[PDB]
Image (cartoon, rainbow, N blue to C red; front, top):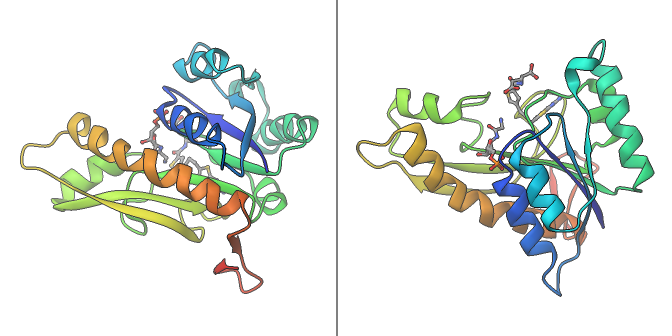
Amino acid sequence: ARVAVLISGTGSNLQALIDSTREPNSSAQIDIVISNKAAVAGLDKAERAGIPTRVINHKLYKNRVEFDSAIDLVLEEFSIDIVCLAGFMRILSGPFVQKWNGKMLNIHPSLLPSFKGSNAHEQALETGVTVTGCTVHFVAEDVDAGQIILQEAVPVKRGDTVATLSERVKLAEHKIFPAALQLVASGTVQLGENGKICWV
Ligand SMILES: Nc1nc2sc(CCCc3csc(C(=O)N[C@@H](CCC(=O)O)C(=O)O)c3)cc2c(=O)[nH]1
Ligand SMILES: NCC(=O)N[C@@H]1O[C@H](COP(=O)([O-])[O-])[C@@H](O)[C@H]1O
């Protein structure tokens, strides 16, 4: 399966996906890295890995569908089968999500359905959970509500900040998101006809 990785920043999840998809048994290949922001370190990680990069600055587009259509063009150009959102921070438009229904994965730094949104760690610490985690889910139109592929719990330690908690959670993220990509790329998991996760 041909994979596009959409990034917005540092790209540590991208790096974990690169490493896993170069394993001999990997069923996924990363063929393009799209960043909506220039000079983010994720572009350098891809360039050091030989992977083509495209920057598609969302601020240059009139609305969301024009920005998404620009992404979709690169995806068709590279004949992409699966899209991974790895720290990509722009909410995607309905028609784009519908087109890629069942082919788009997102990594979210909480145990969904808890702490949806852009600052899951802040919410987790504010709430005082002692267990958080990360979620790989299929992207549905409703943000952070698509079907869940894999999760992994991560303890919150006394004294944790966003810095120490997200560093611990990212260790789990870099496990389940390569695993989740492999499940989908190998056709082991799909969004079923009933819309829930189907382990075929
Ligand atoms: N249809 C649909 N689109 C998307 S995009 C995505 C991955 C990112 C999740 C996210 C969760 S809050 C936030 C967000 O607030 N984005 C802001 C920009 C803030 C920033 O630049 O840091 C905005 O777009 O205005 C993005 C998941 C997802 C989905 O599940 N369903
Ligand atoms: N709403 C999604 C979200 O908050 N994304 C989170 O941003 C970080 C990006 O790190 P990276 O750029 O090093 O992969 C990751 O923790 C990812 O789960």
